[PDB]
Image 1 (tube, rainbow, N blue to C red):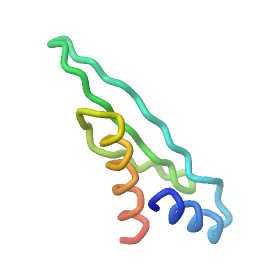
Image 2 (image 1 turned 90 degrees about the horizontal axis):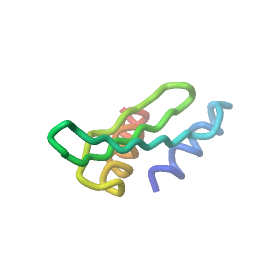
Image 3 (image 1 turned 180 degrees about the vertical axis):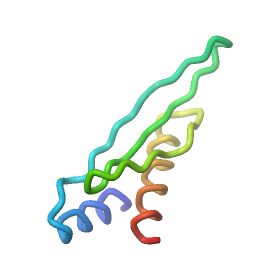
Length: 70
């Protein structure tokens, strides 16, 4: 839903399609965490670090969507 809304926004603004980027992060203490970010119109909205990639994804989606709807 968030990706579709962000895409429709980009189209209305004549901007490039939303760009989703994910990254897996490991610490020196062997702590696995996932982060993601969504670029809208060249403006990057980065989500919070989570335990799973799926949680990281929806986190980035929430951040980007809310920021656009802010």
